[PDB]
Amino acid sequence: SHMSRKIRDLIESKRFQNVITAIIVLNGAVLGLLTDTTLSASSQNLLERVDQLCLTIFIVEISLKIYAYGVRGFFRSGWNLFDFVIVAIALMPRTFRIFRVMRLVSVIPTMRRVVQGMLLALPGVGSVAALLTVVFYIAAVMATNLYGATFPEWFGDLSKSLYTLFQVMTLESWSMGIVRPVMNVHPNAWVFFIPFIMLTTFTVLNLFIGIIVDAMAITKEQEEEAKTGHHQEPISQTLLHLGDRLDRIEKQLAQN
Amino acid sequence: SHMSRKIRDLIESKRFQNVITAIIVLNGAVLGLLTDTTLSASSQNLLERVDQLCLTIFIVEISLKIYAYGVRGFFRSGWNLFDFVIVAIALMPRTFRIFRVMRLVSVIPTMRRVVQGMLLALPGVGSVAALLTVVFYIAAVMATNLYGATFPEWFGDLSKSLYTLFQVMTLESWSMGIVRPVMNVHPNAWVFFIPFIMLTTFTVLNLFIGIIVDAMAITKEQEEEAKTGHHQEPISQTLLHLGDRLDRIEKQLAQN
Amino acid sequence: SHMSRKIRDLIESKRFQNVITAIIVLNGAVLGLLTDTTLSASSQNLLERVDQLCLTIFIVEISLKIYAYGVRGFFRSGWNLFDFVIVAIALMPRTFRIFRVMRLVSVIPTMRRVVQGMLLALPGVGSVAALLTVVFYIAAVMATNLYGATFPEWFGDLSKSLYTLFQVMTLESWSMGIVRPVMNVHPNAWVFFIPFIMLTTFTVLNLFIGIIVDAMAITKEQEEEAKTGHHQEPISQTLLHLGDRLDRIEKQLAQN
Amino acid sequence: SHMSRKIRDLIESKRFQNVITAIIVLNGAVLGLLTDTTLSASSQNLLERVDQLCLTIFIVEISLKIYAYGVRGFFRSGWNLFDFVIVAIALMPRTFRIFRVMRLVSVIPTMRRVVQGMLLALPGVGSVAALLTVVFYIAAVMATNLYGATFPEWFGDLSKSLYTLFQVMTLESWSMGIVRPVMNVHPNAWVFFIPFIMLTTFTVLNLFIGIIVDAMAITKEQEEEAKTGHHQEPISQTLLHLGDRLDRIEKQLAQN
Ligand code: NA
Ligand code: NA
Ligand code: NA
């Protein structure tokens, strides 16, 4: 309808986006002020009302989107569902209201494209992430059996071992705090910890670089399609089209 | 034979892979439960029997593979030999039973391709890895002679020096824990430690990046061959084929 | 005019650049000597006069540039404005005189091209930098509310939380110094800190790699234009020109 | 001459290289044994004679090379000069005899090519390395003036400041050990240290990545020339040759 189209044109405008962005910033700003324990009862009540006002605007915003697009229809987009879930959860009296500042990502298209490039890059690194999970699980079992009776605060159970192996992987006090004390009791403990550090720091870097390279390439195409209407074809496809042109030229030549 | 082909078709199926994967997970799960020191005698005996059941399945699995393929023949693949070695070692009554969770890598083709890309990338970085080994050995000898008499816990012998130089390379308490105390006795010790850190962190990063770049390219070809039957030709070869087509066109033209 | 052209040719020469570079180095050298608290009154007065001499040369240098180019005109370049701002601020009797050693960057063209490649690369990473800012802000609010009453030195207010979350992101004593003590009171604190470390170290690396890749490509073009007069065309444009040549050949052929 | 050619063919052989490599390893092995303080007088005297034997072989090796190639002539190669300098310095009775294990690099061609790729990559990163030097110098002067009177062990002079800023850049105890104690006296010290960490870790990574990318590409060409006799032409040159072929085809066509 004409009314549905007039609302969709209003929602899709730059001015509507700037209003919603400003209210997300305002809501984020009042929640950060609400962390201040020294505030008076009146100052806290005022900020709580400003938070209530920001939330009511988001309910009106989402409701306008459900009418202008539909109920099949708005919910067909993961970014709208995320925006709905975040505002609908606040209407049910969890505790972490500051998570609605994540809406900046969904409302700003350039930020939205960066995050969807990272999410689309995750399937392609799943095998590397599973290999890291396997290495961590094997190492956690070994460390519990080897050092749990002598160092129970760090290796007393599987949970404790997973925690201190994550610490060891991040190279945080790994030697002065963990392995030099462990070696005072188990002199050959370096045989376990030095290869564990070599393997996990390498795997983590591999996983991170895999995400960065894919996400950069994916975002580069999404940004191109959002501006021009399409993306740049790969060099291999351009060389195939050039090769097909050479085949068409050779076919037209030598005969007819 | 018809029986050998029916077994090979069963082994190569997706359902057989999912059964073996589930039993590896189950075995890994019971071994992690066996780390719990608070367990009763009955609970431990039950898990030990479940571990025995998982192992007997793997013996039947490997035996089925030796019949369906051969004895020259199954052992012609490094992934089958690895699977054989890991299950045959358990039948000899070492201590680290959790290493059979590494079978997930050999059983899942996507994980198998990630690991073989990393292993195939190792020869190409051997010279960088040897340079790191040389720098570490030279530095360990120097540090033993320079600081061993005054700091014997850290540099008393070659083994102690290799250990604390690995710690220094990982930047773990390098200054507050090692070099500021060493400098209280040897004021110019920074002349040794700051270039050592500059050289080794650089070489380690070079080695790691070398593996990541090669492994990514190698896996990209192995994944392509496993799905399509072949891999994408390099841009230089495509440009050579295009160049050869231009030579064939020029030869057919100007004369005949 | 002939005088204006003779000054511009003097300014643009290699010898004038080497004189200005030497005076920047000299000024930097005397300021580093002025950090020495053990210096006599005469030694300090001498260095203060040498600093005064270096500054008067820069005033003459800038004044020569304003005459040889203009007042619209010299100030049309960001590198000249930076050079003007840095010398004009010294004539107003802030405290950090050593910031004029940054002039080496503006005076040496190779260093100037490296820095402008980094600055030109910043817009393209703005969305990633904003995502990091959002994650840090959300995390700072959460950490203040969760741990501020029990750990006020680290999380007592928003400012304190932003500081210790930056420390946590850099992996500095994150576990032995912050999270193991926090977990003694809040056993599930790892649920907050381990994903925060995973997200921020990843985002920081993404931001840094984004700057490095773009800056390298941008500098590579600026260095080419400064030497040859132009830069290398992209492979996609070269393939488009080759494709356009094949279209012109096919059009000239088959007819006329 | 026939004798000079027979020696050059002996020097250039694989067997001569394997003998020299074995003696370098042997020399390195005895020097590592000489770090052992518990050794008897006879055991030490024996190893000292083995070290003397290894050195005499190197003198004969270098002397054979000076005859087979010349005196203009052997010294025309940086790798021969390095080999000469390292063996000639031992004949003058400095202290660090283990530096002759660096000869492995010069004797093994694959290791030699890795190191020359790194050295050839250094000029191209000189501007980034100078920018890091400038930032470190400015920061060292600022930190001496700001914190030297209150924290003289860390910032008492320029040398002390350069040392603890290098520590801060490596993120080693930067907060718990340096900046939290400094902030107890100077509450706004984070304004200096957090941007310093942001700038230097970024610049170091930029410098390291710049070396890794260039060194990889340079070694890839040197390895190709050492095996095939030449290196692979860039994609831009191949596209220029293809473009030149299209120009020659178009010129031969439409007329004659
Ligand atoms: Na650290
Ligand atoms: Na670190
Ligand atoms: Na640390």
Image (cartoon, coloured by chain):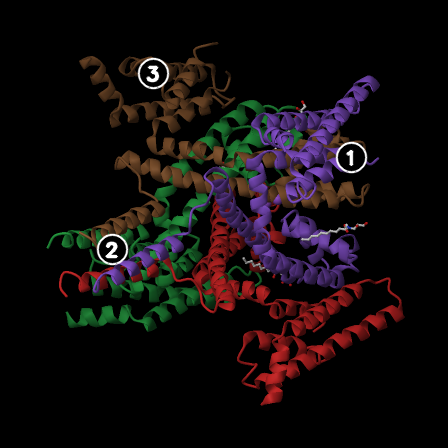
Chain colours: A green, B brown, C red, D purple
Residue B62's tag is 3
Q: Residue furthest bottom?
A: C1
Q: Amino acid at mark 1?
A: Ala
Q: Marks 2 and 3, Cα distance to the nearest angstrom?
A: 49 Å
Q: Nearer the viewer, residue B27 or D204?
A: D204
Label 1, on which residue? D90
Q: Is residue C150 above or below residue D80?
A: below
**Alpha-carbon neighbours of circle 3 within 10 Å: few (<14), some, or many (≥20)?**
some
Residue A75's tag is 2
For the point 42% across and 55% down, the residue is: A99
Regarding residue A178, the answer to whether it shows in the image is: no
Q: Marks 2 and 1, Cα distance to the nearest angstrom?
A: 79 Å
For the point 89% across and 67% down, the residue is: C40
Let me know if marks 1 and 3 both belong to one chain: no
Within the displayed image, which quadrant is ligand 2 positioned in?
A: top right
Residue D170 as seen in the image, left or right of residue D247: right
Circles 2, 1 touching at the beta carbon (< 8 Å): no
For the point 37% across and 30% down, the residue is: B112
Exactly how many numbered labels are in the figure? 3
Q: Nearer the viewer, residue B93 or C166?
A: B93
Quarter of the image where the N terminus of chain C is located: bottom right
